[PDB]
């Protein structure tokens, strides 16, 4: 049974710096993508997925173009106080449309001075 | 991501009995098709899907001729074929989305009717 694991329950960054949010999966099946969101409800802001792109501030920390890769950590650049919140790494399964299969437990991000 | 060898647009005439919309992934590593999923999208709908795990193709009744050649899929060829009557009545931009296990990617091709 797949596990989506965010090792950091909390991240603390200075404003103007990058923030790294960690996520790893224990399996690459079932078939479907990992995406990052801020928030968990229907108002959640899509933060990252692998499709190019429209994510000028968010970037993959690993070699996610490789089949073997089970890490889906990301770096968010030029952190501002508006970026503070709870970020989730979520696994989907393919369909018309795709469905949410499993979520990480959350990483609370805070911006310090 | 899955990465693509991209074509901006393809053109066809009435002489084309079957129209092909190209889609070529350059870093496919799958050893079994059960690992792959393909979606072709047109004006906000999936006009063809291939679920590898179930080995099931699905098209709507107005794209009834639409298909891919599954034997070419593991080479990264996800090109869509359809007949001219389905093609002429559905010109515009198509989105090819390919997934292999957890890696994904998409690309867009404009299907054009030209004289
Ligand atoms: C239609 O036929 C022409 C010439 O044979 C070919 O170059 C073109 O790619 C075909 N178009 C499509 C969409 O398959
Ligand atoms: C998949 O489906 C086709 C029919 O679309 C069938 O002929 C084939 O035997 C099936 N199984 C596999 C493993 O390809
Ligand atoms: C398809 O996309 C291209 C991108 O340049 C655009 O110019 C064209 O008008 C689009 N076609 C339709 C039918 O929306």
Image (spheres, grey):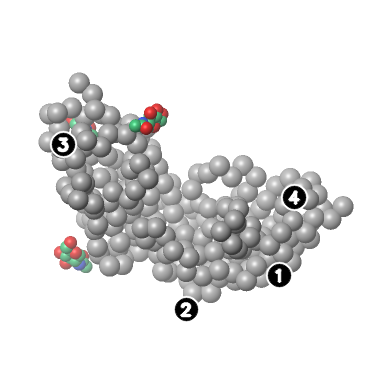
Marks 3 and 1, how far apart at CA? 55 Å
The tag earlier along the polypeptide, 2 or 1, is 2
Subunit bearing disc 1: A
Instruction: Indicate the quadrant where residue A95 lies.
Output: bottom left
Marks 2 and 1, how far apart at CA? 22 Å
Q: In the image, which is nearer the foreground, mark 4 or mark 1?
A: 4
Q: Residue at x 19, y 40 (%)?
A: B86
Q: In the image, which is nearer the foreground, mark 3 or mark 2?
A: 3
In the image, residue B27 above or below residue A12: above
Callout 3 environment at 10 Å: few (<14), some (14 to 19), or many (20+)? some
Q: Is residue B58 left or right of residue B96?
A: left
Q: Is residue A92 left or right of residue B68?
A: right
Subunit bearing disc 2: A
The tag earlier along the polypeptide, 4 or 1, is 1
Disc 4 and disc 1 in contact, CB within 8 angstroms: no
Q: Kindly identify which residue carries mark 3.
A: B84
Q: What x and y, as percent, mark residue B112? A: 28, 29
The label shown at residue A1 is: 2
Q: Kindly identify which residue carries mark 1.
A: A9
Q: What x and y, as percent, mark residue B82? A: 19, 43
Q: What x and y, as percent, mark residue A27? A: 48, 71
On the same chain, marks 3 and 2? The answer is no
Callout 1 environment at 10 Å: few (<14), some (14 to 19), or many (20+)? some
Q: Nearer the viewer, residue B75 or A59?
A: A59
- Examine the rendering and report whether any part of residue A33 can be seen: yes
Marks 4 and 3, how far apart at CA? 52 Å
Q: Secondary structure at mark 2?
A: loop
Q: Kindly identify which residue carries mark 4.
A: A82
Subunit bearing disc 4: A
């Amino acid at each position: 049974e797949l596990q989506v694991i965010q090792p950091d329950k909390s991240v603390s960054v200075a404003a103007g710096e990058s923030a790294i949010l960690h996520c790893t999966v224990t399996s690459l099946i079932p078939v479907g993508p990992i995406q990052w969101f801020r928030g968990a409800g229907p108002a959640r802001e899509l933060i990252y997925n692998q499709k190019e792109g429209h994510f000028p501030r968010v970037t993959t920390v690993s070699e996610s173009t490789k089949r073997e890769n089970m890490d889906f950590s990301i770096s968010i650049s030029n952190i501002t106080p508006a970026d503070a919140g709870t970020y989730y790494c979520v696994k989907f399964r393919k369909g018309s449309p795709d469905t949410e299969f499993k979520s990480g437990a959350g990483t609370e991000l805070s911006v310090r001075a | 991501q899955l990465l693509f060898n991209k074509t901006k647009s393809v053109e066809f005439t009435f002489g084309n009995d079957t129209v092909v919309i190209p889609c070529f992934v350059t870093n496919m590593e799958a050893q079994n098709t059960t690992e792959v999923y393909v979606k072709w999208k047109f004006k906000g709908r999936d006009i063809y899907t291939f679920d590898g795990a179930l080995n099931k193709s699905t098209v709507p009744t107005d794209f009834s001729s639409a298909k891919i050649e599954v034997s070419q899929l593991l080479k990264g060829d996800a090109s869509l074929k359809m007949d001219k009557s389905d093609a002429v009545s559905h010109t515009g931009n198509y989105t090819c989305e390919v997934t292999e296990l957890t890696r994904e990617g998409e690309t867009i091709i404009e299907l054009k009717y030209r004289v």
